[PDB]
Image (cartoon, rainbow, N blue to C red; front, side, top):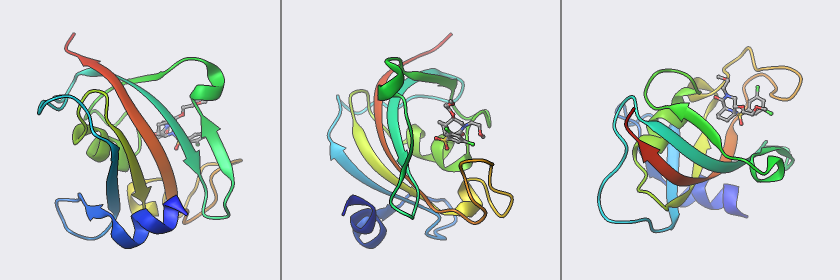
Length: 128
Ligand SMILES: COCCO[C@H]1CN(CCOC)C(=O)[C@@H]2CCC[C@H]1N2S(=O)(=O)c1cc(Cl)cc(Cl)c1
């Protein structure tokens, strides 16, 4: 399925090249511009665990998730991955635990040492 495909066929987008964050662009976005550090970014996403279960979805809440990029407001994989996206892009990200919740996890939902899979749509970005 899609998690296997990004695992086996995705691009390593880490500066370290440590295969910690892998990406496939699923729906090509607009032009060339990506958000810059500190921009307010609006996304829709879903997340799955490696047991095959969906653990979260913004779609199901009927509103996007909004954060300030590159500030550590989200897991490292998200700051890295969203920074690569164009407006309107949909991607798949595979996030090893070192770029997510690590050995601690985040109970109740995120186990220790969890590799996370996301589908992410970048709706918009704006400077404040
Ligand atoms: C109901 O909350 C939905 C948005 O949750 C964020 C949680 N965070 C920030 C806090 O942890 C550092 C995240 O970084 C990531 C990525 C952004 C979207 C959400 N997570 S998540 O999908 O990995 C997530 C979802 C849920 Cl339901 C619980 C936990 Cl612990 C993480």
